[PDB]
Length: 277
Length: 277
Ligand SMILES: COc1ccc2c(-n3c(=O)n(Cc4cccc([C@@]5(C)OC(=O)NC5=O)c4)c4ccccc43)noc2c1
Ligand SMILES: COc1ccc2c(-n3c(=O)n(Cc4cccc([C@@]5(C)OC(=O)NC5=O)c4)c4ccccc43)noc2c1
Image (cartoon, rainbow over all chains, first blue to last red; front, side):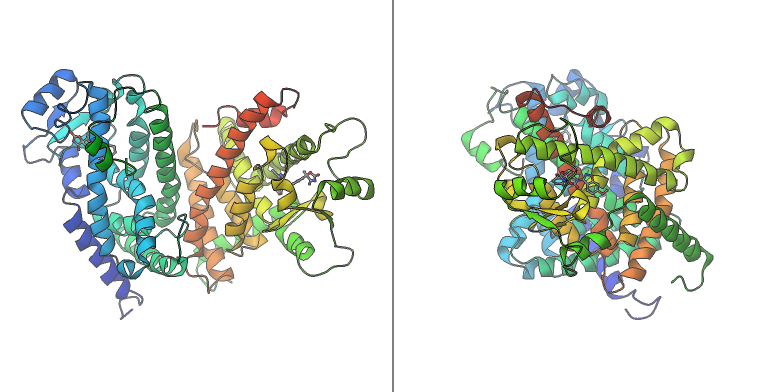
């Protein structure tokens, strides 16, 4: 807290540290994603998926990350897309864990508490980050190479047609807050350091780090958004919305798998892609 | 304790008006509840119900809110307790409604939105307020004249066995924040004015009132708890725990509605449970 206000030095160093770590861990930033979604893409437009024919072409042309399960699982599109999101979600776990280790104090916590914080936090972070690739009309696919429309995802078979809708509804409201990457970098760090996680052995250093992160975010929002009145409080309220998407996703995994006979892929693939959904 | 600034001054006057209305609307405050639970063991001492035998001995001794004149009971302990809590929730709706009308701007809102704010606000408030009446060992009952143990409530017949546990678990963590009646007045007003409720016609006028309630809650907590670093952020995150209790209570009632065909549900609560998520 050396001059400027004061209490604008250790907190500003923490804010900048997280921002740099976030840029390093998550290459597709909100800034880069918005440029594509608004049309400032520098005439390098993403491939649009609006129906089955465009999906078929994108798989051959762009060669998406979800083209792979055309050798282990069924040809059913709705199942391939749903499992593809599951595969990306498990891939994201590693990006989030690398980011978490860069949070001052996180590596010094009890090894079991680190596992617990990442286990319950990753899903809340996935949905927060997913908002950055979404607008009212769709979502950016595979590193911004494609754009899958909201209508196409809604056109999907009986249980799968409603899977992306809760994330779209949240995204529209979360995006109205108009946060940028430097804001998100601190918000995701606050999510990880949640002291109410079940099975936590030593809550004290967790809440101590989170309180320091909350102070850094409160300041970040006041400096970057002076006109957005209670932006900090409004953002904290969105953690209710995040937790609800997570609880609803768990309900869907119960509706499917206990109605879905089309298996869950190769035994080794099933093992790699479990729990982190 | 504003100390200059006409902005801080308006927020203090708002905090003052809300605390005033809360005292007028809710007869059993947290302050009174704590005085009964802790020290002052004279005319304030409650009768303790810890087993089936003590419950029977209690009805004959002190005339509680569950043993009113004429056949209005159920002639079965587990159901009788649950029905009493159901009737108390109806009375609480009248108290919360009275308090809701005192929040500046609430009565000015579209009538349909006034109904939706209360439909969803009610249960989250009952549970927040109920924490004031609890400790880890039990709950104050019949206007603080009695005290029912957590263990006697946990030991009830099969469908009612777990019924109070999510409330007691929430109360333990919520009570750890050490909020007083003056903080609760603002927080419950913040809960009612939730712009993210389903079916709201005009979100913007609700959000504007909530923004001002959040500003008044932030100042209140900083002045009343200056040694409690991020109390405001910790309090806003508890709104997630509130939502989960509601979801479980509703799920619990669906089971009761099927297994207990002869148990009546109040129309007022039936309208509340209706299109609830
Ligand atoms: C940067 O931080 C982030 C940002 C985003 C995600 C994320 N995620 C995501 O992108 N979608 C939308 C989507 C839709 C369709 C196909 C695909 C994929 C898998 O299939 C395809 O062909 N391209 C693909 O990307 C992806 C998700 C949908 C659901 C859950 C997580 C999703 N998981 O983890 C993340 C980390
Ligand atoms: C705004 O402040 C508040 C404060 C509290 C409540 C509240 N509530 C509550 O008090 N309990 C605990 C309890 C336990 C046992 C018996 C009884 C009663 C009803 O039955 C009996 O025999 N004696 C009794 O008091 C009451 C609840 C339990 C469940 C739901 C709501 C409950 N509903 O609404 C409120 C508004």
